[PDB]
Image (cartoon, rainbow, N blue to C red):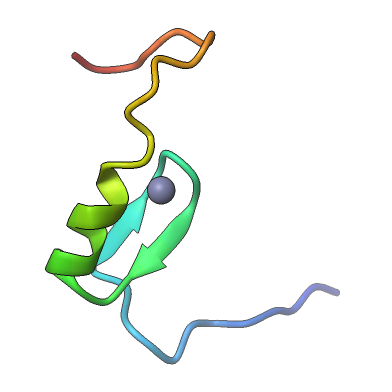
Length: 46
Ligand SMILES: [Zn+2]
């Protein structure tokens, strides 16, 4: 029926903003400073 990749690695940090995983609490930080711009779309939590 259906099948795909399970995810051997572990992504304890995800970026819902875009949808990418990060295996580093530090790396994600620098990345978090990317979706700052106030997109034309309404937020979700502030
Ligand atoms: Zn992101």
